[PDB]
Image (spheres, coloured by chain):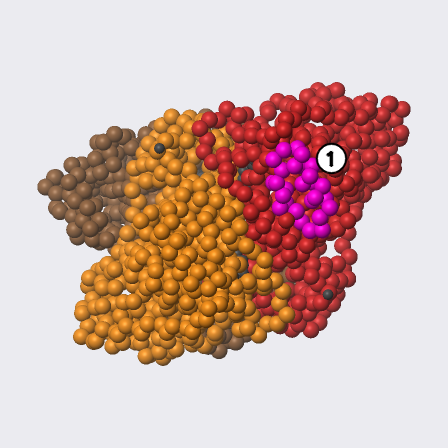
Chain colours: A orange, B red, C brown
Amino acid sequence: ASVHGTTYELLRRQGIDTVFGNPGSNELPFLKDFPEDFRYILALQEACVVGIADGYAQASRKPAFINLHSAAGTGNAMGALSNAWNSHSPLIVTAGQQTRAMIGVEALLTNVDAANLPRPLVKWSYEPASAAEVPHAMSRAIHMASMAPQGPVYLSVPYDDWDKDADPQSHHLFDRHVSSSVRLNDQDLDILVKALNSASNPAIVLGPDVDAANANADCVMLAERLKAPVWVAPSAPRCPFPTRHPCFRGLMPAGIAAISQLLEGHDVVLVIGAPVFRYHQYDPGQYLKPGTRLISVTCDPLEAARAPMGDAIVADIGAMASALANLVEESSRQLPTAAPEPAKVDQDAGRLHPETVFDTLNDMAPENAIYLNESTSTTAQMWQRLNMRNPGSYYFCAAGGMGFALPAAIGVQLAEPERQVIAVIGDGSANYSISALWTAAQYNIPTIFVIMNNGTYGALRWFAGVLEAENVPGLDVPGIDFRALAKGYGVQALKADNLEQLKGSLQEALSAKGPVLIEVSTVSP
Amino acid sequence: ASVHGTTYELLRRQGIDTVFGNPGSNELPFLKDFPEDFRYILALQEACVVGIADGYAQASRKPAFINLHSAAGTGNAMGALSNAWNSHSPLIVTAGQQTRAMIGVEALLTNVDAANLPRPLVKWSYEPASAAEVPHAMSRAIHMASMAPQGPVYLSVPYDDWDKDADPQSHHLFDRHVSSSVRLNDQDLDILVKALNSASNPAIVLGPDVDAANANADCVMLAERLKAPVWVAPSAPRCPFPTRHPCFRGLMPAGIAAISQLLEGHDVVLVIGAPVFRYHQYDPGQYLKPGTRLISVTCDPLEAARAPMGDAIVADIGAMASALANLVEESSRQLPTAAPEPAKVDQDAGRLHPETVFDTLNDMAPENAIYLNESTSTTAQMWQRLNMRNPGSYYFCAAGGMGFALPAAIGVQLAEPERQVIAVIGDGSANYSISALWTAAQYNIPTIFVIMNNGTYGALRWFAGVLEAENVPGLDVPGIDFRALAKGYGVQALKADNLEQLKGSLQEALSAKGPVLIEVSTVSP
Amino acid sequence: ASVHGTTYELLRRQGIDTVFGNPGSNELPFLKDFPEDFRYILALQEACVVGIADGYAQASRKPAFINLHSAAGTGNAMGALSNAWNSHSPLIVTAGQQTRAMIGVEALLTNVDAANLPRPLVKWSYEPASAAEVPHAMSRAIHMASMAPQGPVYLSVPYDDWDKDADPQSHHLFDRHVSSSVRLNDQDLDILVKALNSASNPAIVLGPDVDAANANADCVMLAERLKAPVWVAPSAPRCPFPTRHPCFRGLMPAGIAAISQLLEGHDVVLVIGAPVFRYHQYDPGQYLKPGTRLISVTCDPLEAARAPMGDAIVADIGAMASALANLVEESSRQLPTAAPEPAKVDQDAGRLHPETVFDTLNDMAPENAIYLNESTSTTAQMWQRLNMRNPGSYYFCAAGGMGFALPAAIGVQLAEPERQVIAVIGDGSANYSISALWTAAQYNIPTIFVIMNNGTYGALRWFAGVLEAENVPGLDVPGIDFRALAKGYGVQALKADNLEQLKGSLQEALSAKGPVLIEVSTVSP
Ligand SMILES: Cc1ncc(Cn2c(C)c(CCOP(=O)(O)OP(=O)(O)O)sc2=O)c(N)n1
Ligand SMILES: Cc1ncc(Cn2c(C)c(CCOP(=O)(O)OP(=O)(O)O)sc2=O)c(N)n1
Ligand SMILES: Cc1ncc(Cn2c(C)c(CCOP(=O)(O)OP(=O)(O)O)sc2=O)c(N)n1
Ligand SMILES: [Ca+2]
Ligand SMILES: [Ca+2]
Ligand SMILES: [Ca+2]
Ligand SMILES: [Ca+2]
Ligand SMILES: [Ca+2]
Ligand SMILES: [Ca+2]
Ligand code: NA
């Protein structure tokens, strides 16, 4: 067998059937004779390739496979890799290298010092020392991306390797099963459960690894048994809990003092599946107030090591959430009462307030919609106004890096063809990965893109206010026609300058059979 | 003085007055109170920011200063950095880091292991250990980017550093002058000159560092004195010689055997300002034929070390080209005769052959036009058909990475406001950095963009033919309307479906007062 | 509080009370005012500092703390770090940096690019961005070294940081408890247990992480219930099983084909606490024969990813070994019968055969002796001839790197003051870390060092035979007087040129109250 045949066999035997890619000439010997059981999803720039694969992996809860061109293609994808690192996304990033005979001379298209290029944003990065090693290196990449804590990996392969003979012993790679589905030992788990049962006023804080593990329903059972309020850890990349459940308390503020004030009076705070904590603004004060202790369950040793307070347990989130939910006692405390509905903001017949947009989306979208957020100044309102009952219903760029939501919404829609995806993206953020629209058109992936057009980088005006920073250049983005950009890439486009037109465009988009972009005129900050 | 005030003083005293950027919140404390003597050039994605700065640096022959946001902004720019590394572009890339007090907890927007992120594509990469060190670290960045061999550098700065007090001794940085303008010692230079004077059939091969050094006119004098044919080294990022001078022989084929066959019969081959060599296709055979010896003058030790044949001298290209041109004897051999004009290819009233497009551009463009090339299947025809008499007249992505020419054409036009820039870009390549069009519109930078629309990644069909690779996915890019994309970003747009409309659109574009995009329907390969 | 006071408080609250070090001037501000409850163990070169700390950590099963001088001190220790990486040793390596104000100028003693220096041999490597961050960075180092898979970490600290004020919130670091004591979830564990109960001819292979976890006794119970033969995985750094238990089958040969032939006929092979596998010689063939399947339990994702065959479970070895030993059924198969005693080799009245030395050590040493091995050509005989009943009884350089056993034997003896340590070290290996002898003398740590003096690098003659390599320089080491080297560093020294003198020197050494070196004249290969 050739290295090409053996490597595609390993991929299919490990459950991989889709290649997300933008091709080049070091990759043609891999892509030739492409197997009939695989698909190839082309995107026009590599941030878009990786964003699409990232949405697909996060929504499918399985690894996604990427093929990029050498150093320039890998490099175009590195902002997308920053977000994938912070969302623990299992991405297998492959890139083609020059033929071994010209690597030393640094022929055009040589990826020099290849394994160092995507560091520090990958768990494992490698170029094999011979062609026969390629299937074993691919096996390492698959398992490194997929074991907890999941994350992106990188493999560079000289183009001449594919046609070489494979090692006949590579068949032992095909059916390897590797598990990291582990939980705390019984004695120490019993100690944790007794601490939770004994707490007088527990709180629960949930992060994105809960949604990645599909541990959401176990966390609902846990919060119901403990009768405990539930927040989402700050800077949230995913939604880990039903947002209209009575225990839900919303997104935590991303500040040290704000969080310790929020948690004041809670004797035990159990954090599951989150870093402790993804603060943003600098809000110095106490990490926790006197009387509060914190316990974190995390799948990632790096998160356990860096927490500035609390105890930690490094284990699988699905296995731990299931065990805790089934072992804790039902408290005789009263269940928390649901938060009140948000108020309706006053809306005239002109430009839309973001609050009006989210209320109208909540009124009209299906109950199993999936939302993505890259409208950076409106996140708090989005979390207050969208009822997200089901797992896998929310994604936000985990490293804060623009350029994620537009392509990731296409990958999520490909992973979840029966759930309508609605990406809410600012006019600033929409540009970073605008060419991803083409992939939605070409493959007829029916994502809805709602562009919140207020003419400016609104969140940077907000943060400038926090810093009291004046005379800052580069904050306005006037003069972009998003219906013409959508037409450029083959996507149907609608405009909404007022609430009547917002309702009409959403009705048309929800009834459409392909992707649709709606440009919404929103109020200037 | 504050670190902010001291750092902007150092920049202006070192000749920097423009910041190319896409802002974020770790950068607002640097950008606030932006000095009145500086400009800020916004672009909507970081590949575009860096591409624009790269064109500006290459055309101005001076360092360009960039400010990006943390890891995601730096990462979005890394394919642009791959090209800048291979063009020796002096780029000072700065990125903002979180406040020092939250780096350890990895707050949102922390650039983890920052200095390792852009490696291996930078000459120097650093984050200072204290605020007071920031001006000295910036001084190091300026000089590292600017000394031979020039190239990109990276500096990460915690946002809280800017408002701190500067070291009063930082004033000694402001006027430092650092020179690498060096040439081979007199005794060894005299040995080289005697070898050139004694050659019976010398050849000259020139690379991009000749054009970077503005050594073009000295190389013309050298070739006239030696009566020697002149080629351009393969995979050329720049044009180092007048293309209709009698000595000019064109772009070398990018293959080992093809180059040694071309050079057969030449006893001494002098390479100036090029790697030896940027081969592309694998074309194994002899590096040089018996009877040919090679001497390379390069500004880059890495190029001298990796050449597989020949002697080398590591020195400044401007200083060496001037010395050689003024020291060699005038040979009594006959001057080489000019190559014949290219033939006119047959053209019907339908889609345009690329040969027709380049002939029409050569007929209509000013004699001091500047061309950029990212039309990958038509490079050989472009080099045969455009008379480029002057330095700084051609740029092509030096690492072969798509996404360079569209933004770089805007930076070159900003650097050379009296020379019309004409970027010839394939329909595939145009997508990688499409949002750069917005910067041309907003600042009214009057670049002309000629999009060669043949519906496919034509060069990858070519390379697939070379490999005899069949059943390759992802090679076609149908369904893109480039006039709608140009309208989306505010640029005037024209279409040319035949030769009459090509001539009319070029006349309109050359008479326009702002940027113009022309979509040309070209023949399918 | 100062950073100095807060950092020593964090260390003591996390169970650290000993600093292994060789001092320098960047470290004096850390070491000044050394707390009365800490000890400092000086060694004269940094390979020896780290080797001693490594033996101490491995034997105590807890992290050991090291302080080295800048880049040169760290660099002198990097061969010791290679062994610590492959033994999963929890080492917290700290090094002093220049004062922040002169790092940029690269004053003498600046550790440039410090965090990159010990990579790739550490799990985590860092220099803090401010003085106040130092206690949190130390907390990260402690937990990163101690969480599974354990391993060395590195922290560089500018010397001016120690006297600065600490962050008042650093107290939340002092009592953090972090656990990685996890095992496979109940459903999948029940599947594994049923596979073991159903096997017709199971085998068990154990590696060093069994001894690190003190899982040895649980593995004896497991092998007794399964009635299964037990081997030790190749290139063994530790001894994980009693070597005269009836199930014990010895050290596996370090070859691919040799291992699959050994395992032929075993239907399920359970590997616990080992890489799969640390082969050495290249012995190509099948990884496993038809009819054998392999299951690996490992604490290290990198080991699970790279195994070329089998299933894997990534979990804590102590927790998994305990669960399996208590859940499997007692098989009705007959218990394996003990291997026969090794034969006595013929010994004349001259130089000693290694077999005679190990038989005499086994006859005379206490039953709770601890052995170290750096006598590279005699490993197989050592494993056959020493009855090691107890955990923690054997150490061998895990990366194969010379210079481990001499210093590590001193650290093991410090960790286990009531168990006699006997280091068996070749005359070649003894030189690499010879100055460690001084620390044993100065602190009166009563290690016994048995130097096997055959005048040559015996194992390299063996491997040269395997390669059929002739005319190799550098294999002989004549002319070393080890009793004079021991006298040089203050250690009592004895010579044994025959068996009578070997017995007399061992009796004298076992009765001594301080360290003793015995130089044994062994037969030339
Ligand atoms: C890759 C990248 N570049 C720049 C930024 C900085 N950035 C920018 C540019 C923001 C403004 C996004 O504007 P928008 O129009 O999408 O939304 P708002 O107007 O609601 O803020 S928010 C933010 O952090 C970033 N985070 N990531
Ligand atoms: C960043 C990046 N991604 C992909 C490629 C691979 N690539 C691609 C995609 C080419 C086709 C460009 O198509 P075009 O339409 O611009 O021009 P032609 O049709 O004349 O080839 S040429 C080439 O090397 C690349 N070099 N750089
Ligand atoms: C740091 C280092 N340097 C060199 C070696 C190579 N080496 C050497 C030099 C060996 C010979 C050790 O000789 P010895 O006298 O200690 O024992 P034998 O004579 O029994 O082999 S075995 C071996 O792998 C090594 N592994 N580690
Ligand atoms: Ca099919
Ligand atoms: Ca906006
Ligand atoms: Ca001005
Ligand atoms: Ca094309
Ligand atoms: Ca004391
Ligand atoms: Ca020896
Ligand atoms: Na990198």
Percent position of residue C358, x then y: 32, 42
Question: What amino acid does circle 1 point to?
Answer: Asn
Left or right of B81, for residue B325: right
Residue at figure coordinates x 53%, y 73% from the top left: A466
Q: Subunit of mark 1?
A: B
Q: Give the total of numbered labels.
A: 1
Percent position of residue C253, x then y: 33, 35
Q: Nearer the viewer, residue B332 or B474?
A: B474
Q: Is residue C450 above or below residue C115?
A: above
Q: Is residue B322 visible?
A: yes
Q: Is residue A136 above or below residue B485?
A: above
Question: Image quadrant of residue C420?
Answer: bottom left
Disc 1 crowd, CA 10 A, few/some/many (<14, 14-19, 20+)? some
The stretch drawn in magenta includes residue C229: no
Question: Image quadrant of residue B88?
Answer: top right
Percent position of residue C45, x then y: 52, 55
The residue to which callout 1 is attached is B362
Q: Nearer the viewer, residue B441 or A290?
A: B441
Residue at figure coordinates x 64%, y 23% from the top left: B257
Q: Nearer the viewer, residue C423 or A519?
A: A519
Residue at figure coordinates x 27%, y 54% from the top left: A182
The stretch drawn in magenta includes residue B508: yes
Q: Is residue A96 visible?
A: no
Mark 1, ligand 2, within 8 Å: the answer is no
Q: Nearer the viewer, residue B396 or B496?
A: B496
Percent position of residue B244, x then y: 78, 31
Q: Secondary structure at mark 1?
A: helix
Residue at figure coordinates x 13%, y 47% from the top left: C329
Which region shows up in magenta?
B493-519
Q: For the C terminus of chain C, which image quadrant?
A: top left
